Image 1 (tube, rainbow over the protein chains, first blue to last red):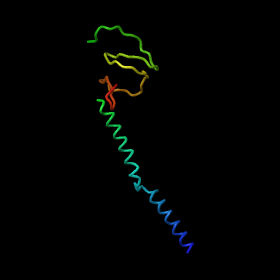
Image 2: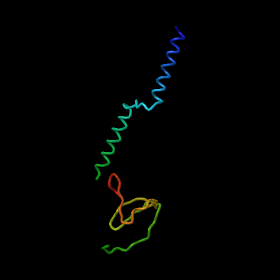
Image 3: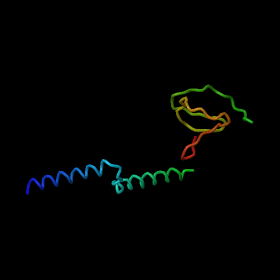
Length: 49
Length: 50
């Protein structure tokens, strides 16, 4: 069943490509770190007033 | 009111001292391109410096 397994793998790679090429927000775990670090720096800057 | 101290020249584009009506500090005085509204004097930022 090598040809069937090849076509299923290609279809799965294409569906991963589609769900990333759409506007589905999937990198939230990576965006959280940037948001928390930026917010901590903004609070540390606003403590000077 | 403007207490009695003699004024000097305005030097730009290099790290100098300044004193604008009591506003002491140290920095580079580059000319700007953003017009105020004609009743405003200061300007501030997130840390509330000029």
